[PDB]
Amino acid sequence: AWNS
Amino acid sequence: APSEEVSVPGVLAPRDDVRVLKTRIAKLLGTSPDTFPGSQPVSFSKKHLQALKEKNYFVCEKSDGIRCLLYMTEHPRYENRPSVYLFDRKMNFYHVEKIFYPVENDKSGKKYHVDTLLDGELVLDIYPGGKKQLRYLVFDCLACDGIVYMSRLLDKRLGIFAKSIQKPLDEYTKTHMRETAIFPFLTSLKKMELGHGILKLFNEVIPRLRHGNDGLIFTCTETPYVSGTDQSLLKWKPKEMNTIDFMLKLEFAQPEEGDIDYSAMPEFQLGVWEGRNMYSFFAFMYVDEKEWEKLKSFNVPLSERIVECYLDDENRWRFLRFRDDKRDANHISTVKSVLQSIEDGVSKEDLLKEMPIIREAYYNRKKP
């Protein structure tokens, strides 16, 4: 559950 | 559960001592007191392959440990008291009590060295039985017995150290066993090969080391000692040395029907610490079935934790060890820097292929  | 050395034997010296020391060394070498007089290498790139063909070089195994200069002088406080100080690139001075350095052909044994600055590295050797031994490997000498050899070349810099320091130390060591066994570490000259002796280091020297290793060091024997970044001093490292710490996340795909089978191999997602609380997806960590069954053999939580990874020969990140100490993964800046280090630099193959040419070019410019 993170960016990019 | 893979996780995780050496430390300076001395104790941090008081400020009103390290200031006097800084001033003394500054007056000796003719540099700024707060400026580190030691040298720092540059990354070995492609343009250096030609360099090794144009100048005489010395190659040696780049041991991993603490790089720090050794200083033989008199104690700042007490007038006549032989003292030895170890200081790193951050100018942190450590007073090494319980050590001495014999003077050449000294009958009495009361004579001692002053104004002596050596450049070396602190490593930890592993002897049979798990018995450890701290060691100091000298690879250069800035000043010896009051004379500054920084203007001279490497052969003389190591020569004077060999004559006035190492040889009397060995002479003393071979006769006095119990006396030598009390030393905080063993001082010795580092084994160095010719610039084209790379192969010999790979198949003979390195695999028989008693301490860790990460790459090689090329020291030009035709250049004077230079404080700070040295263009002649080259540090080479294979691709597997450039390790990055990521945040590991195990992504188990949602099955078509039934509960998620965790025995099946998931997606090993690696994340990079960007902001303060924000991470970002970077790449995948390759794991085969044997390695996967190996990971489940630990019976420890695998997801949501820092891991150290390295680029294999197939350019994919493989698991190395956990990082229980690290609070966060490597910052995007560090990651970028490491990626640049991997992108640049010469491969082991392309470096080896140039050795027979460096050898002949060396013997060609040789002095009759």
Image (cartoon, coloured by chain):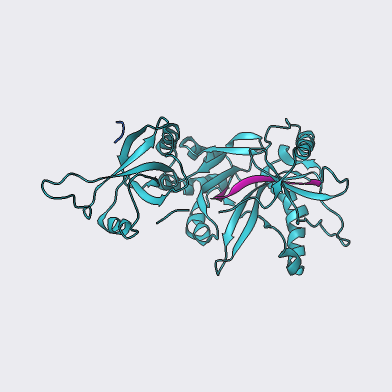
Chain colours: A blue, B cyan
Instruction: List the single residue furthest toward the left.
Output: B257
In this rendering, position of residue B83 left or right of residue B206: right
Question: What is the magenta range?
Answer: B59-74
Residue B137 falls left or right of residue B312: right
Q: Measured along the vertical axis of the image, is residue B229 above or below residue B138? A: above
Q: Residue at x 65, y 53 (%)?
A: B136
- Which is nearer the eye, B203 or B194? B203
Q: Find residue B234 and report its horizontal and vertical position in percent.
A: 54, 40
In the picture as drawn, the residue positioned furthest to the front comes out as B259
Q: Position of residue B49 (x, y in %)?
A: 48, 40
| Quadrant of the image containing the N terminus of chain B | bottom left
Q: Depth check: give the residue in front, B17 or B290.
A: B17
Count numbered badges in the picture: 0
Whether residue B30 is in magenta: the answer is no
Tell which of B240 and B268 is nearer to you.
Answer: B268
Predominant secondary structure in magenta?
strand
The residue at 41%/42% (across/down) is B245
| Residue B84 falls left or right of residue A2 | right
Q: Quadrant of residue B337?
A: top left
Residue B239 place in picture, x, y as percent = 41, 45
